[PDB]
Amino acid sequence: ILTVLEQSQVSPPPDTLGDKSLQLTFFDFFWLRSPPINNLFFYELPITRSQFTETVVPNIKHSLSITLKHFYPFVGKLVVYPAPTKKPEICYVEGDSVAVTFAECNLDLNELTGNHPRNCDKFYDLVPILGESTRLSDCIKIPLFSVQVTLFPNQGIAIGITNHHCLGDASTRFCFLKAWTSIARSGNNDESFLANGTRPLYDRIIKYPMLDEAYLKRAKVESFNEDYVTQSLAGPSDKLRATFILTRAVINQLKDRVLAQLPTLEYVSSFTVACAYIWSCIAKSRNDKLQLFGFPIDRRARMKPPIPTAYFGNCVGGCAAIAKTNLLIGKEGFITAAKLIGENLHKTLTDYKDGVLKDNDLVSEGMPTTMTWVSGTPKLRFYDMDFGWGKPKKLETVSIDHNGAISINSCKESNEDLEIGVCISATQMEDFVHIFDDGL
């Protein structure tokens, strides 16, 4: 089903980059022990094996190489030292490279790019492993970014991107991908990027050393080297992956229902309404006791003073709500969900305005029987990423399979519509589909 054509290593062009480091913040240290992030971009095009070898392979290598000279941390490694003093950092050293795998897949591409339930494990051999760590006398070094480009002969191409969350957040990945695609589209040339594109800002403008040290303690840094193990996804599995669509029209109707029933609810957005609806579906599907639902927040614009969009690295916050499952079910359940999300998000955003940077409560108050954390930021249009073959047919966040997570992103026939990705056991999928569709 999968054939590896080439295992390559891609570096910046000769005589372009010297040794370079990037210092990290508490926002980055938060993710020290996180599993890899895996994303797929699927493209439809009538591409032959010969053409893939002749132009695609060299074009991927060349365009990535050129992009790396502007995005040094992508070709660097996370370096963790055993001493509680020396902070982890990103280091690039001359000779460092990005692992780029070229492969061929004999599965029907049309059996992967749809929205209906497909086996989760069919996607695993399309995403690259993050890569083996390097263990030295004074440190461990972990790769930050890897790529797989997979040919589906006469059908298209999937680009699988795996990264460590310490490299940066979704905004950082978006910035990088905008550059890479520009460079690829313009025939392996950074002239357009340098003139018109958004360059990464490596200035260390987030300086809170006391928070830095507090976050490293929580992430247990002295045992990191001893504890670190690879976390690649592998089958077989009975789980199914589906994509659920909330159209602008449906979202507005749901929003109108919330605003009508709860006229003084301080925060109601397309995103909170989408979250509330999926939240209610998950509650109905699980028929459990107590649930937590949460999601990330890009904090850049909310910082005091504001952080430029192009700031390189992590600048992410989070918000969560907890409710008894019986309160989340049905039409009234969706309303309750929207209320709790809205209230908690309003509180969180007020705290950011006040300049609040920080943030077994559960053991005391009650252990959730389900927890869901959203992957995704619908504001970032990953569906516009065009390497020269057109925009993606389908995006998948494969790493939601690891734990209590769903993906929420914009669509590309419409940036006002939302796509929700779910990977759950086959037995639960059948009901979930009916729950979602019937409820609308």
Image: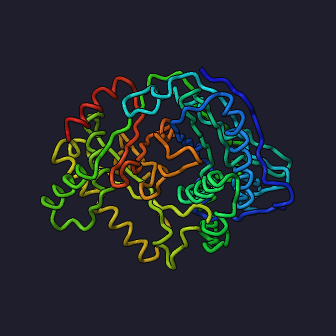
**Of residues 60 and 79, the one drawn nearer to the viewer in this rendering:** 60
Rendered residue at 69%/53% (across/down): 74
- Is residue 23 or residue 418 the one in the foreground? 418
Q: Position of residue 411 (x, y in %)?
A: 39, 48
Query: Residue 209, image x and y in percent?
Result: 64, 71
- Report the residue at 55% width, 24% height from top: 235
Q: Position of residue 213 (x, y in %)?
A: 64, 65
Which coloring applies here? rainbow
Image label count? 0
Residue 318 coordinates in the image, percent (x, y): 44, 58
Q: Is residue 30 left or right of residue 433?
A: right
Vertical order, 35 against 94 (above or below):
above
Residue lying farthest bottom? 305
Query: Image point 74% across, 48% down: which residue?
Result: 62
Q: Which residue ends up furthest to the left in the rendered image?
A: 261
Name the image quarter holding the N terminus.
top right
Front residue (pair 8, 311): 8
Residue 269 sits in which quadrant? bottom left
What residue is at 75 percent from the left and 33 percent from the top? Answer: 7
Apparent side of residue 145 relative to residue 379 in the rendered image (left or right): right
Q: Is residue 266 above or below residue 305?
A: above
The answer to whether residue 217 is visible is: no
Residue 346 sits in quarter: bottom left
The answer to whether residue 73 of the structure is visible from this angle is yes
Rendered position, 36 above or below 83:
above
- Quadrant containing the C terminus is top left
